[PDB]
C-alpha cells in the first residue's frame, strides 16, 4: 500500500457511490468495509460519514447506505463479539461505532422503508429477516422501523 | 450479470 490508500479510499468510494444511480454494487461496499476493517482506528468518523451519507442523498443511497451499514455493522459486531473487556482497554472503536448507529438506525430504516416502493421495501424486509435468521440479533433491538407497520405489516 | 458487482447480500459482510 501507499499514502494514496489512506482514508481516501473510503471517502472516494462513498463519493463514487453518491455519483451514481441504481445498483448497489458490492465492490464499493468491499472498499468501504475493507478500509474500515483494515485496522479499526476510526469509529465516529466512519459512522458519521455513512449515516450522513444516507442523510444527504436520494432513495438509492438510503438503500445503498443500509447495505453499507449492514456490511460494516455486521463485520464490526462479529469482530467486537470476538473480543472482550477483559482483553481490551480505552472504550471507543467499532463497539462505539455500533453504539452510535444505534441512535440513528431508527430513522434510517423507517425513512428507507417509507421512501421505498414494494421492491425496495421487500429488500429491506429481507435484510432484517436475514438479521433475525442469523440469530446475531435479538428482540427490542430492531424496533427501528418504528414498529412492524413499515415493511413488516405488508 | 446482475445489478450488483460483485454480488452481495446481508447473508455475509465478507
Image (spheres, grey):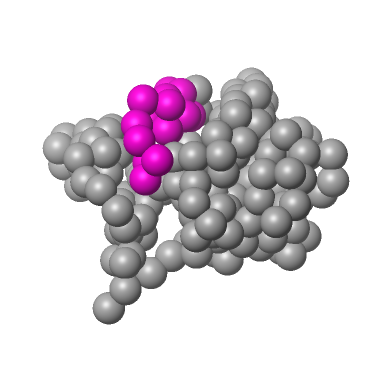
Left or right: A123 with respect to A24? right
Quarter location, residue A5: top left
* A101 over A19 or under it: above or below: above
- In this rendering, does residue A69 appear at all? no
- Vertical position of residue A37 compared to residue A107: above or below: below
**Magenta-span inclusion, residue A54:** yes
Residue A115 shown left or right of residue A109 in the figure: left
**Is residue B12 found left or right of A138 in the rendered image?**
left
Question: How many numbered marks, from 0 up?
Answer: 0
Name, please, the residue furthest toward the bottom: B1
Question: In percent of the image, x 66 and y 62: which residue is there?
Answer: A130
Is residue A145 among what the camera can see? yes
Q: Quadrant of residue A103?
A: top right
Q: Quadrant of the C terminus of chain A?
A: bottom right
Identified at 25% across, 48% down, the residue is A21
Give the side of residue A120 with respect to residue A59, left or right: right
- For the residue pair A111 and A32, the one nearer the viewer reads as A111
> Where is residue A47 drawn, in percent x and y?
48, 29
- x, y (%) of residue A112? 52, 40
Residue A19 lies, in percent from the top left, at 20, 40
Dominant SS in magenta: helix
Q: Which residue sits at x=63%, y=56%?
A: A125
- Of the pair A88 and A5, the residue shown nearer to us: A5
Question: What are the residue bounds of the magenta stretch?
Answer: A45-61
Q: Residue at x 66, y 50 (%)?
A: A151
Depth order, front residue of A9/A125:
A125
Q: Position of residue A77 (x, y in %)?
A: 64, 46
Amino acid at each position: 500500500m501507499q499514502q494514496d490508500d489512506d482514508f481516501q479510499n473510503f471517502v472516494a468510494t462513498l463519493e463514487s457511490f453518491k455519483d451514481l444511480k441504481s445498483g448497489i454494487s458490492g465492490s464499493r461496499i468491499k472498499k468501504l468495509t475493507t478500509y474500515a476493517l483494515d485496522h479499526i482506528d476510526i469509529e465516529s468518523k466512519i459512522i458519521s460519514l455513512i449515516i450522513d451519507y444516507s442523510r444527504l442523498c436520494p432513495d438509492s443511497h438510503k438503500l445503498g447506505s443500509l447495505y453499507i451499514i449492514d456490511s460494516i455493522g455486521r463485520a464490526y459486531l462479529d469482530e467486537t463479539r470476538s473480543n472482550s473487556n477483559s482483553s481490551s482497554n480505552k472504550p471507543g472503536t467499532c463497539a462505539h461505532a455500533i453504539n452510535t448507529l444505534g441512535e440513528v438506525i431508527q430513522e434510517l430504516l423507517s425513512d428507507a422503508i417509507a421512501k421505498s416502493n414494494q421492491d425496495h421495501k421487500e429488500k429491506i424486509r429481507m435484510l432484517l429477516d436475514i438479521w433475525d435468521r442469523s440469530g446475531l440479533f435479538q428482540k427490542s433491538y430492531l424496533n427501528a422501523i418504528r414498529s412492524k407497520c413499515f415493511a413488516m405489516d405488508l | 450479470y446482475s445489478p450488483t458487482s460483485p454480488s452481495y447480500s446481508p447473508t455475509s459482510p465478507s
